[PDB]
Image (cartoon, rainbow, N blue to C red):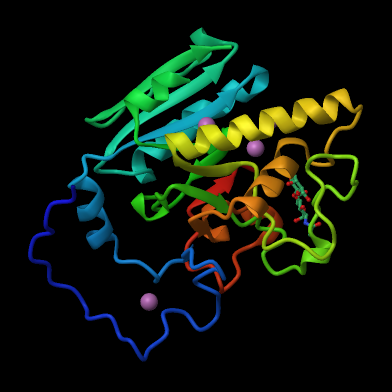
Length: 263
Ligand SMILES: CC(=O)N[C@@H]1[C@@H](O)[C@H](O[C@@H]2O[C@H](CO)[C@H](O)[C@H](O)[C@H]2O)[C@@H](CO)O[C@@H]1O
Ligand SMILES: [Cl-]
Ligand SMILES: [Hg+2]
Ligand SMILES: [Hg+2]
Ligand SMILES: [Hg+2]
Ligand SMILES: [Hg+2]
């Protein structure tokens, strides 16, 4: 049950004025493609706060990667879901190496040394790589049952150029005449149920490949792409959500660089 939104004053949407004329803002299966300018964050914040939404953010930090936690968490505190309940889940082999980061109210962090728990603690799960930093707003506009993110190196490429697994012997196999986009393995999410279904499917597919003596060209990411090809995401995030300024610069098509690789 969703309660009524309160009176709100904002610019009237214009039916005869396209949102963006330079990019595709909706997929052929009617899933929004999230770009700056396509959403009014005030309306979305209201909708999700009225639901008392809790977002889980998971990251794996093994060995040397634990050194990326401080910047990752510090910037997440400034840009990730500010205003909503957030639960960070840090999976690491070095519990004592996790930095003591100051968190805002309503936000907590759990260190898990290396899943029904997720179902009772959060509404959505966002899974990302730790050797990154938030540089701008990453909010509720991304929340949906299942979302994938456009790889910054292939968003303007033809499917034939996508680095999908091309060997029929692999469960991640995708022929040259199939494929919508090339999604990143480093940033996906959705409801806990959908995320667990995706990870469960990926795990099983990778076990089958292993038994068959084959490893997908881009490992987990290859299987992620096969999954999202057969189970269309309900929202697709633009490259604004995972960029590498050192390697790709800052093109005009990107009004904001929200989450980026650390040089
Ligand atoms: C079109 C192209 O060759 N782009 C490459 C990127 O692919 C590459 O980033 C890697 O991409 C592969 C999949 O092709 C994996 O996702 C890997 O994890 C990425 O690091 C970048 C950086 O090497 O260089 C170009 O942009
Ligand atoms: Cl992840
Ligand atoms: Hg718009
Ligand atoms: Hg996850
Ligand atoms: Hg997997
Ligand atoms: Hg996967």
